[PDB]
Image (cartoon, rainbow, N blue to C red; front, side, top):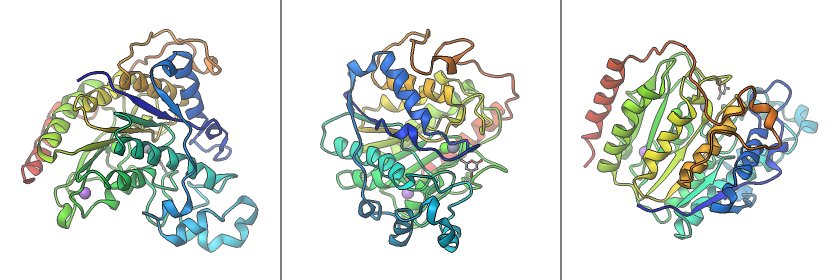
Length: 369
Ligand SMILES: Cc1cc(O)cc(=O)o1
Ligand SMILES: [Ca+2]
Ligand code: NA
Ligand SMILES: [Zn+2]
């Protein structure tokens, strides 16, 4: 279907935002990703844009006025005066107050919405924003290290010109905030693959299928610890092929959270970078306008490898396994290679479990017109 035009979004300030001592979310990983892919030469093959800052008003296309007014006002120096509001909006613990919090949200969001506009205008085939994908944020509260739902805002932009939009989420966590926003409409189908059972955020059972006009337009594949490349590959291409056939979307959003990789500080899966990136290859073959976003990922050397390789896949550009010199070279020892090995952890997802869940999801997809 030909090679694709790619527009990529990055702000050089993004890596300086700091969630605080000990916090696993590290914006620096987006700077590591950028520096690695520049050193592979991938800037020669794509257009690189700075995101604009999304305004408070633009954010209220989804979020409440009261929540956005609070996010644009709260600072470490005035926290004591805002104790009540912090609790209501779920800020100040897992989702801390840090210097420049609102600006970080504006740049994360700006990349996703700018990419959506470029796709709507038919000025690109693919848009990429590795600072986006913050899928847990809700209408009026922060959740799961996410404050503003850049994904929901980008999908609302795509819906100006697309009757049906497909959302796919390969982060290890359930895409709860995106699913909730579109739970009662058939104009967005949401498809999430995730660890389920005594795990954050607690939602995404296979029996969660949507409601009202949106019944059968939410799809959830719950998984156990230790899934590997073979098992994930067993089910991803067949599921997405059936969704494409039945739903017939005109645009796609793919959240590429890297916390589903082997060795993640918070995750419990066993995928390689090649296994994760096979998902990008499958979605790209349908030749639809595609927005590719970031997400979780807590072992930062592997996040940089994953998103560098997935940028190369979007470009159909082969790159060597030997890493080029870069500003973070020491982070990639002791091997200094791009690709990673799986661990010897047990895969609790039997082949029979994988086929049975797939078969139940196929039953629900037969209910589409
Ligand atoms: C992404 C996330 C958020 C959180 O509060 C706990 C966790 O384990 O993972
Ligand atoms: Ca997911
Ligand atoms: Na929906
Ligand atoms: Zn996650």
